[PDB]
Image (cartoon, rainbow, N blue to C red):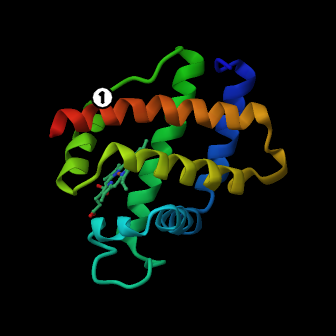
Amino acid sequence: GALTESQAALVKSSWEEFNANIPKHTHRFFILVLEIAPAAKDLFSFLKGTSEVPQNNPELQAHAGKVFKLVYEAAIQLEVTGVVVTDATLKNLGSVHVSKGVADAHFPVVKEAILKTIKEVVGAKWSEELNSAWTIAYDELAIVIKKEMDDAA
Ligand code: HEM
């Protein structure tokens, strides 16, 4: 696809839409995760011991917000510059995932959970050209974190 000026404009616009409702989009995102894969629950400190996904847990919200921010920032950086840049933060991210027991086959779980989350977020504006734009940005960012986990292990 690339990342035409016209595609990037379409990711920005759809991220602004996501941030606009963190407690919803973030608890949604954790349920689409547990639907695709239920066992994933024991991994998360704030989900252990619970029977259901807490809806107002600040620990969970702050956690899932930081996740989507990082995908969007990736798309713009691809249209301007042509790439996704690896920094300290992406590296520390790779360590914590490993401590907690996370693996690569967990990633399509979270991608489908994010495309389905953004198709749910943009509704009728959805275009091929947009799906094509977030797919390219997640795929490009996951490539980068998987790379750093492997390195934290
Ligand atoms: C591009 C994709 C991904 C991004 C951008 C991302 C980002 C993050 C961030 C930023 C943190 C730490 C947040 C904090 O300090 O508050 C974190 C923690 C964690 N991540 Fe991910 N993540 C990704 C994929 C995954 C996958 C595929 C899994 C597996 C299900 C996973 C499981 C976890 C767990 C268990 C923790 C620790 C939570 C704790 O017990 O408190 N992540 N992630």
**Residue 44 appears in which quarter of the rendering?**
bottom left
In this rendering, position of residue 2 left or right of residue 52: right
In this rendering, position of residue 31 left or right of residue 50: right
Amino acid type for the residue under numbered disc 1: Asp
Residue 26, compared with residue 74, is above or below; it is below
Q: Measured from the top left, where is residue 93 in percent x and y? A: 27, 43
Residue 70, compared with residue 58, is above or below; it is above
Q: Measured from the top left, where is residue 110 in percent x and y? A: 47, 51
**Residue 13 appears in which quarter of the rendering?**
top right
- What residue appears at the point 44 percent right and 33 percent down from the top-left corner? 141
Q: Which residue is mark 1?
A: 87
Q: Measured from the top left, where is residue 99 in percent x and y? A: 17, 53
In this rendering, position of residue 142 left or right of residue 46: right
Q: Secondary structure at mark 1?
A: loop
Q: How many marks?
A: 1
Q: Residue furthest top?
A: 82
Nearest the camera: 70 or 143? 143
Quadrant showing the N terminus:
top right
- What residue appears at the point 60 percent right and 35 percent down from the top-left corner? 135
- What residue appears at the point 36 percent right and 70 percent down from the top-left corner? 41
Pointer 1 local density, CA inside 10 Å: few below 14, some 14–19, many at least 20: few
- What residue appears at the point 33 percent right and 26 percent down from the top-left corner? 86
Q: Residue furthest right?
A: 124
